[PDB]
Amino acid sequence: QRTVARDITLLECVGKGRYGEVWRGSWQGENVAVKIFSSRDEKSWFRETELYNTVMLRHENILGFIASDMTSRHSSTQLWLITHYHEMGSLYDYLQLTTLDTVSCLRIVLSIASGLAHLHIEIFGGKPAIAHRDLKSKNILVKKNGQCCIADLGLAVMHSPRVGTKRYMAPEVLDETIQVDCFDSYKRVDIWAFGLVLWEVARRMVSNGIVEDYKPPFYDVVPNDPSFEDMRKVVCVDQQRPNIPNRWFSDPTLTSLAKLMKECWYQNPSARLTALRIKKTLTKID
Ligand SMILES: COc1cc(-c2cncc(-c3ccc(C4CCN(C)CC4)cc3)c2C)cc(OC)c1OC
Ligand SMILES: COc1cc(-c2cncc(-c3ccc(C4CCN(C)CC4)cc3)c2C)cc(OC)c1OC
Ligand SMILES: COc1cc(-c2cncc(-c3ccc(C4CCN(C)CC4)cc3)c2C)cc(OC)c1OC
Image 1 (cartoon, protein in one colour):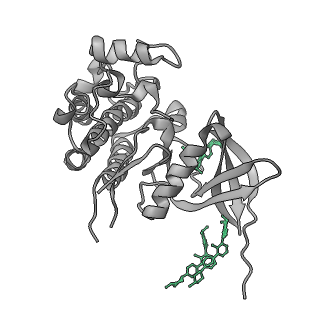
Image 2: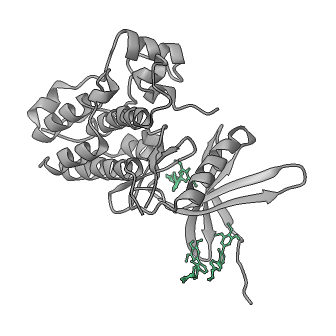
Image 3: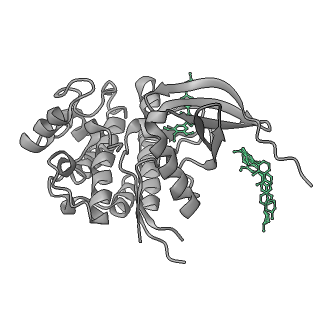
C-alpha cells in the first residue's frame, strides 16, 4: 500500500552537551534538526513528546515539531526529537558576532514575546496554557526572516528532575518561595527570564555608533556555571539586576526597552508584566 521512508541522514553535529547532541539531518531532500538524547535527559524527551501528543503546537515563533522517535537497540533505547532546522543557529550564537539596528532588535524581541504569549495563553475548543521553565538565549533560534522561535519544551508545564538554567532563575525559584501549585507562578518565572534575554539582545543594538559586547546576564557578579547559592545571593539577598548602560538613555528604543526589562524584574512576581502586555508595548515602540 505505501513506503514509509524513516531514513534520516545525520550530516553535521551542530551541538554536543550533557543533554546529548543536535545534528543537521536530511529527510527526503528537506533539512531537519535531530536531537539525540543522553540517558541522563530521557525525561526531557518524554515531556516534550507528552506535550505534543496533547497539543500539536503550530506557531511561527515556536520551533516546528516534525517527529518523536523511540528505537529499540541491543541493550538501550534511542530517543530522537526531529524539528525544523534553522541554519543561523541560536540567538546566543548569533549575538556573539552580529550587531543589530532598531528594526532587527525589535523584530527579534517581539517575535520572542509572540512565541511566549502563544505558549502562555489557553485557547478554548485550542491548547492548554503552557509555561516553558527554561527560557534563555541558547533555547531561541534565529530564522532566516529575522524572527526567532522558542525551542526545548522538556521542562514545560501545562494548565487548563531537570531544573531551569540557574543563571536565568527568578528570585522565587532561588529562595524556594514559588507557589508550586499555582500555574501563574510559572508564567512569571518565564517573564523574568524573558527580561534577561531582552537585556542580552538590547546590548547588541547600535545607537550613536556605540554597542556593548555580548555578555550573559550577571556576567559581572557570578562565575561561569554559577551555583544555586551564587545566584540566590545576587538575585534574592542583594536584589541586583543587570546594569542599564548610560548610552541607552540617548536612544528612544533602548530607553523604552530598559523600562520593559525593569517591569519583568520586580521581586514581587505578581507585579511583573504579562507576555501579552510586553507584546503591546513592543508594537508601540518606534
Ligand atoms: C513512522 O516513523 C516515521 C514516519 C515518517 C513518515 C514517512 N512517510 C510517510 C508518513 C505518513 C504520514 C501520514 C500518513 C497518513 C496518510 C493518510 N491517512 C488518512 C492517515 C495517515 C501516511 C504516511 C510518515 C509519517 C517520517 C519519519 O521521519 C521524518 C518517521 O520517523 C520519525
Ligand atoms: C512528519 O513530517 C512530514 C510528513 C510528510 C507526509 C508524508 N506523507 C504523507 C503525509 C500526509 C498525507 C495526508 C494526510 C492527511 C490529509 C487529509 N486528512 C484529512 C487525512 C490524511 C496527512 C499526512 C505527510 C504529511 C511530509 C513532510 O514534509 C514534506 C513532513 O515533514 C518533514
Ligand atoms: C535549542 O534546542 C534545539 C535546537 C535545535 C536546532 C534547530 N535548528 C538549528 C540548530 C543549529 C544549527 C546550526 C548551528 C551552527 C552550526 C553551523 N554554523 C557553523 C553555525 C551555526 C547551531 C544550531 C539547532 C541546534 C534543534 C532542537 O531539537 C531537535 C533543539 O532542542 C529542542
